[PDB]
Image (cartoon, rainbow, N blue to C red; front, side):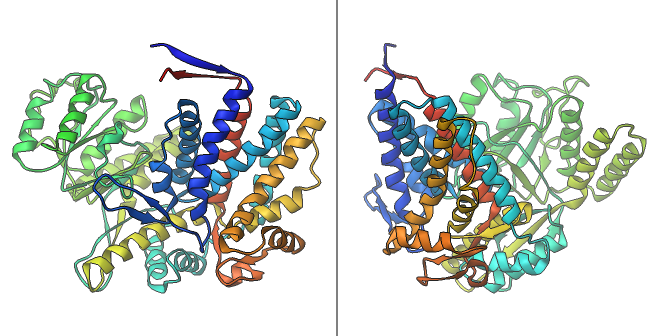
Length: 524
């Protein structure tokens, strides 16, 4: 259709207005003393929330250019949140600061490319300084401390997380489920988590966490891209009559078959989910065979001769539970022959011994680690249903925080890490005056979030920022208690991975926005 096109400054002004609206909607919730925002719903009961991801999802402007700007900023913020587990609000605030200062700079006449180069150099130095400032948390005591901090100073959640990731390992797959007993239960079961997500966002049935959950589902193992429906119709009918959910694992479910699955899901007649196969080439076939063995099923291989039309119910694998996220998909307690598991791991170890290059050795070691490690299940329990649900949510948040921490370490929270980084990098210089202006823009951007937090608290932003800058190390201003001192001692801390991802993605989206010369939008 006809598209209205905006060239030059006005398009950037529209994008700035959109990002300003989004950042003003989101940034109010930032900080422990963060004001809540009301999201009106169609049912009739507004949902008052302080969580940033829901506000980001709900925001959608009517002006096409502002809507596109807000959409791209929200997309990069959501990517940061999913990669790190938190920090989407911080990423949005950083994006607002960089965009505002960069547009002010380019209005003077500075080259957008030089500004982008300066911002990239500044954020690279910021990442280096953050890694230098990061405090390791490899020991179990530090892991328990991080878990306690994340879930509103609760010792039980930290102890549970430490025990789980000491039983299965630092990089082991850990999941949580509703525990019927009052006492929390921690069991290890066979399971696997690969790095593929759902093909269609409409597959989500729990919008609160933005994931897909199936109870006791059948697993379909196919090595052919799915495009038609007629070949999977017998299997779909069989699983529907069995009254159980279905999970389809193939190279790619596309064409009209994906649309058929989507429309069936929104109809709600059958809850079926499909995910892309992990890996490619012979590795993809190997992981599909491993998953089939883990789930106690036989892979439908058209190369061998098996066909989807003739696929039977017994060929499909089974598992206790599966959780699907847009990045990773996890299988919980896949029922299968234990002797088959030992046979598979022994064969993989034999291939490791027979492997020639260290690359193949690493791949086979990853496969055998995924097979042998399994998945730990934290069956959290409490006295009442609502209390147990709240505790499960807190455990999930603390698990994500501890995963990020053990992945990258921990740095002083409350936004003072960026303050320290800016104070240390204030002497950085670029090859041109424009690059120096971009670097100063980045420094003000990293100093912005603490100002936003303290403004939400109510105190003067400039005074608090200057006092934090004057200090050294982890000396910062606590927003909750309205006092200064060490964040690590007080316990206001977040994993450095969250801050690093926020900085990098805000810098990337800001560089994309600054170097935007044109926009194409559908005509209203």
